[PDB]
Length: 49
Length: 49
Ligand SMILES: Cc1nc2nc(C3CC3)nn2c(O)c1NS(=O)(=O)c1ccc(C2CCCCC2)cc1
Ligand SMILES: CCCCCCC
Image (tube, rainbow over all chains, first blue to last red; front, side, top):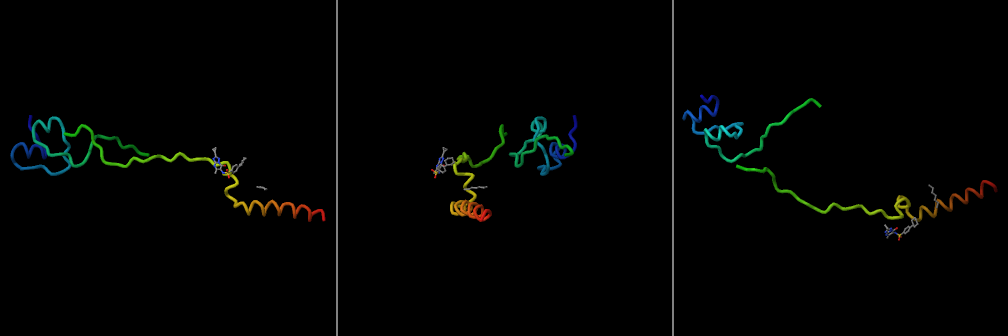
């Protein structure tokens, strides 16, 4: 029940915002407030050709 | 939060190709067809001459 990483820094008031490769999630949006998504990043599978 | 990610794009009419009946005679200009037809026969008569 303790957040680490950038989300942990933001929720525990150690930072004002978390600029980076932060994916919008259900739980993260429950905990912190996200801005509009500025790049679409789902989950995808990479394989050797 | 967006429920569908998309963007602007251009829709155009896909040209359906039309097949002319003279398509196989198209590679050679009509004067070339006439010239080769004349050449065949002049060579043919000159063989037996
Ligand atoms: C302008 C044009 N529009 C056309 N639309 C069509 C379609 C699809 C139905 N064909 N077509 C054409 O073919 C022409 N060109 S033509 O009238 O100078 C012409 C006629 C006929 C022949 C031969 C080809 C060998 C077999 C015997 C007849 C060759 C040239
Ligand atoms: C490929 C040979 C074509 C001969 C046409 C003669 C008119």
